[PDB]
Length: 393
DNA sequence: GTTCGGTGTC
DNA sequence: GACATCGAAC
Ligand SMILES: NCCSC[C@H]1O[C@@H](n2cnc3c(N)ncnc32)[C@H](O)[C@@H]1O
Image 1 (tube, rainbow, N blue to C red):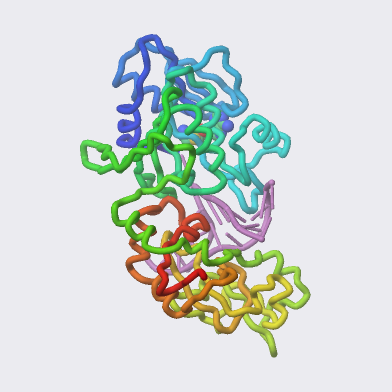
Image 2 (image 1 turned 180 degrees about the vertical axis):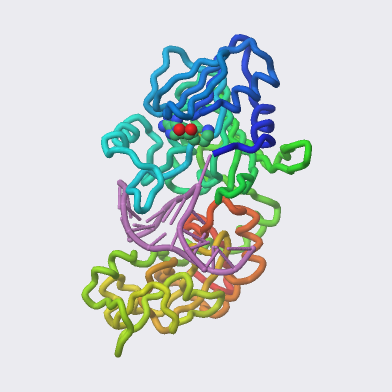
């Protein structure tokens, strides 16, 4: 893993430390952030680097190198500045997840970190650990994925940061070559409060920050790139979550173990549908992408709503809204399934057209950009629907 | 019950 | 770039 020079230079320009102050790089390896800070600001600081792998630790004689797990590390004194590129990844089984430690080690992480939620992430834990090691008024500058701005797993982290000091977020995007990650820079100071959102422009000279919006009373709410247009559209109709009960499909293991499900086609058997069967405005009932077949009438045994024709919205097609009416009522292995609430009048074909419209695609791309490769529930439930498509009596 | 990807594979 | 994970995780 190597952070591009223009990304490092941009983060160092945001970094601050008092003279003689303690500067720390977690997961430092050879320590590119300590070197860049020293070149820019001088030698009159106490430079420290923390690294877990003895093969990776290679710091110059002017920096103190510590062989330790940063997440379970207990230093004597706190730090004035913390900067760097933390490792990213979910801790779990090797067949599914990239971070592999003993169960007892993961238990030590869960115990240490109050923001740990769901599967969580290594970079979330690094963020909380760094804030806890900061002096009052201390500065943190990290480069992390943009996923923590919107996702539920990071709700406690967002609430934590809003409570501990003031936050600036700088959107970079996919700035790491051969790494599938949309990145942001977080500047945190352990004093004051509020959130500042920034866009960036890339030139040959580096990255230039452009102020987008300020949220002085930010309490840990989902972070979005709002405009005059997005606000206008949102108050034009009811939120989609107010009109529909939104459920997700049964998961692959539920189908695989179910006695009615077959691994091969046959008489009376029908394909279990995935996201590859869902298109803007229609459903492909013929193609099988899951490798699973079952009787259509037996679908209600996994989820009761599989027996009722309903609205299906896509989950893994990037940040966009792809919808279709499932007229036939098939078994689904993926996607959102929207069941109208009591007293809700709807026009299925008109609502599908609105959800697939270019106005809606632009709406979600403005707010959520490419933070995640999904349309999430929290994005979906906030989508505006006017009386022409769905009415609540 | 549903969430998430230094994505996974074409 | 297309076109989406899919199952271990809680
Ligand atoms: N800063 C570069 C990307 S993060 C990758 C580096 O962080 C180190 N690393 C991974 N987990 C760590 C941990 N828990 N504590 C300290 N260093 C870690 C790895 O050895 C690797 O050199």
